[PDB]
Amino acid sequence: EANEGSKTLQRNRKMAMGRKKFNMDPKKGIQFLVENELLQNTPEEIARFLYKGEGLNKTAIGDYLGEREELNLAVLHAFVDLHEFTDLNLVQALRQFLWSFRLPGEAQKIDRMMEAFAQRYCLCNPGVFQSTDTCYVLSYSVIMLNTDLHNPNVRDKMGLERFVAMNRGINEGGDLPEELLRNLYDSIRNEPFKIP
Ligand SMILES: [Mn+2]
């Protein structure tokens, strides 16, 4: 006679095993979970698992999201869609996003994440930016500013006035508010990004 409590206990052990396998080798971890019917092999379901992140290494999460593979790309889109950026300013939203995983080192991986982020930010906050290219450019400006201001290996530091000068043109056929740019600058300047 089948004992469902036994089934649950075995499943818990397998899930614990799967998380541990994921932290070593994200694709292997996901394949194991999928094969044992512990996770559905759908972009949305895998994205929900990584967004919850229970006992998952955020560098592993990032590495999974940065694979240039059809499924992983679908997962990255779904994962960014689980974020809630409505009513946040760009730095506030970036802080939420960049807490949920550790960015890969590779520029192309970062780029795909940053494009996805910018498109989702603009959809959640229509009319803040006149295009997604503007928000993409400005999201990099903010990430680079965090690096420039808070990594001491970057010698000479960019001041507010220069940051505003670089970025005021990037909107459309007319500049943004310089209010919005000063707000982003000071935010980063006074609180670096919290990274995992
Ligand atoms: Mn501070």
Image: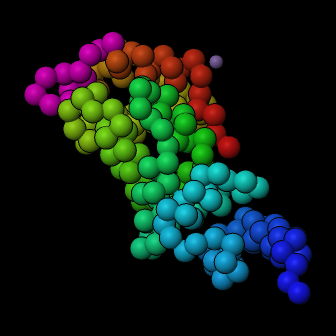
Image quarter where the C terminus lies is: top right
Query: What is the residue that sits farthest to the bottom in this orientation?
Result: 1
In percent of width and height, residue 47 lies at 54, 59
State the residue lying farthest toward the front.
Answer: 1
Q: Which of the two residues, 193 or 155, is positioned nearer the viewer here? A: 193
Q: Is residue 92 visible?
A: yes
- Is residue 135 shown above or below 103? above
> Whole-percent x and y of residue 193?
58, 32
Query: Residue 60: which quarter of the image?
Result: bottom right
Q: How is the image coloured?
A: rainbow
6 and 117: which is toward the camera? 6
Which residue is depicted at the point 15% across and 31% down?
A: 172
Q: Quadrant of ligand 1?
A: top right
Q: Indicate left or right for 182 with 99 as reference.
A: left
**Residue at position x 59%, y 22% in the image:** 191
- Compared across the picture, whether 21 is left or right of 146 comes to right
- Residue 25 location (% of width, % of height): 68, 72
Q: Quadrant of the N terminus?
A: bottom right
User: Total number of numbered labels?
Assistant: 0
Task: Look at the image and say whether residue 70 sits in the magenta stretch.
Answer: no
Where residue 142 appears, x then y in whole percent? Answer: 43, 32
Q: Is residue 77 above or below residue 29?
A: above
Whether residue 28 can be seen here = no
Q: Return the residue nearer the eye: 6 or 176.
A: 6
Residue ID at (55%, 74%): 41
- The magenta segment: 168-179
* Quadrant housing residue 64: bottom right
Measured along the vertical axis of the image, is residue 185 above or below residue 62? above
Q: Residue at x 48, y 38 (%)?
A: 84
Image check: 2 left or right of 55? right
* Relative depth, front residue between 107 and 70: 70
